[PDB]
Image (cartoon, rainbow, N blue to C red; front, side, top):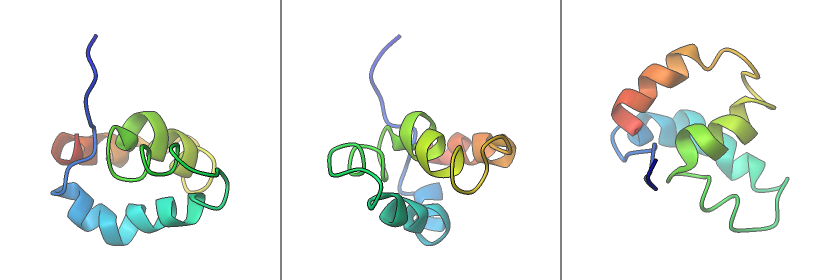
Length: 73
C-alpha cells in the first residue's frame, strides 16, 4: 500500500457543502488532527467516511460514497 488522499477538491467541492460540513461537525467529536487529517484529505474513506458517515450519516450506505471517492479519491 501507499499513503494518499481519498478526498479531492472536486467531489470535495460537492462534499464541501455535503460532507465536509459533516466533518466540520465531527470536529466536535475529536480534538484535532483526526478532524483535519480526516476532514478533506486522506479523510474521504479512512476517516471522514469511517468517522463521519460510518457513525453519523451512513454507517453502511457508503455506496455512493465510494463512487464519490472516484472523484474525491
